[PDB]
Amino acid sequence: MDIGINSDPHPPHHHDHHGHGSGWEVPEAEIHRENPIPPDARSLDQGGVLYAEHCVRCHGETLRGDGPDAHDLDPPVADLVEHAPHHSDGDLAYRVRIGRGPMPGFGDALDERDIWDLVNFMRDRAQGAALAGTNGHSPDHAAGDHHHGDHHH
Ligand code: HEC
Image (cartoon, rainbow, N blue to C red; front, side, top):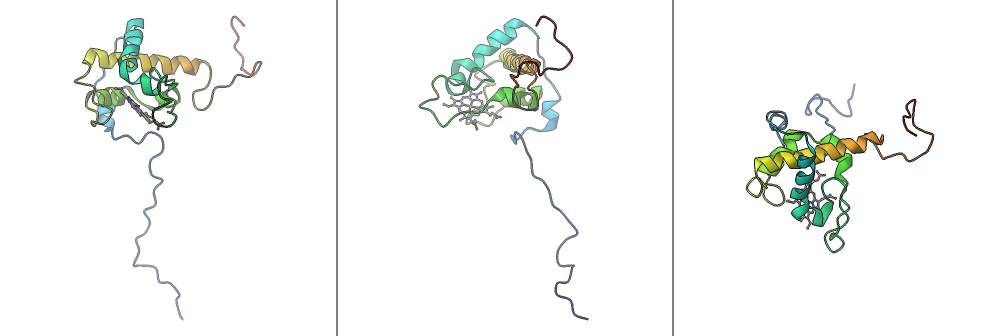
């Protein structure tokens, strides 16, 4: 007989949950297309200096984000070790090489050889942190909580 609100002027439905996690602009195609990474200690160590030369002074060597001279710098920094498994190789290699300008874009500051090292040390470190059994959340330090699997306890 009488309608209070007719359904039509509006569309069927277009509700989204936005993006959660990183958010950085990086085409999935650049993230998964080319990434030459040599897996060694030198890539880890030397790759560890790349970021440590200038980036650690604000947020940890690479993943820790413990920052040594960040006390005067902007508010506390995030922990990349927790977000590392969330970031792919092409993405970090893509950001270090092309970046945007402000912070990333060290493709001219570093070489590809370094870029893979930056990718190696973060990739190795982030993984070593997973061993502790924290991947997916915070690290548990409760003794006698681990599942079946001791080996040298
Ligand atoms: C302070 C003087 C900084 C210097 C020098 C560098 N970065 Fe930085 N970076 C800084 C802040 C405050 C933040 C925000 C972190 C937060 O808590 O929100 C960042 C962040 C990044 C990120 C993003 C991390 C992520 O969660 O995805 C990247 C990839 C990054 N910074 C890279 C980077 C590099 C390569 C630098 C050296 C060349 C570098 N930063 C220096 C502060 C500062």
